[PDB]
Image (tube, rainbow, N blue to C red; front, side, top):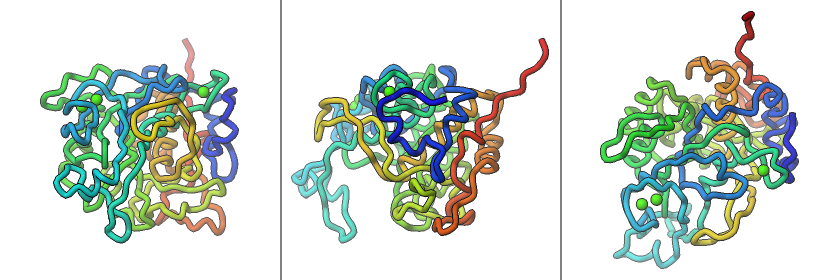
Length: 354
Ligand SMILES: [Ca+2]
Ligand SMILES: [Ca+2]
Ligand SMILES: [Ca+2]
């Protein structure tokens, strides 16, 4: 089954080429379920016309109002106000953004709004087969926006609290989440070995039944160098390109569980360079893009068979992955089990007599 969206043909990651995830075969089984919820734990969302119908009420765990860029600390509105950082902000020695992002040489730089959470959310669940824009992996699934990244990023504590809340666990000062998510997408990370703050939250949500999918990182470095990609009990995802080859930037190593489309990925975005402006579509690169191909595939796996455990989900993802092509720059010790194949991973529960 294929959707009719105008730009779907440019979304090679969904197609059945050597590098693609082979979604049309999966979509013959299921195009998702509104009872399966994927949490996009990220910069927040824009109510893009090609996305908003699949977005649930979420939460905003950014504690610092300066980073939050929305007039307050934690709040119940996960809309993305923009995460831009001006040159004056990053260079102000008396300001809250001083040297908050540095390049290879240790020099500060400025950035426009990324709308990164809107791009990631569109890969999971853009409104599909509606004759416009892009498609998502789960056409009918719901997306729980959990905003944890603001101007110059986010804090470990806010991200770990967002993780707990996303899965339906308690966080002090936050209301209960009536839409617990069974798949949690983390297209983010930072340096250092896996903090106990992350590992405690991960183990709590996994035991609650959630699958945690995390970007391996973009430093052409060992995946051991980036958390939460280097944590236990997560699915770390490396990025490959349209030819099934290792992305130049992807982190690699023994902890990577699978590779997925992460180069030239078209999805929903916004045209604003600071505050929100018009809906748009944009092509991004990163392990951030590979991660929602895997998380969306899990959402379809659960729509097709709601009884699968996180352990069974990982085993099926890896067993159904395609071997890396010759000359890919990938191996099963560096890029996970193979190339993501949703068409092979998604399997309907058994039918039975009545
Ligand atoms: Ca706020
Ligand atoms: Ca907010
Ligand atoms: Ca669409």
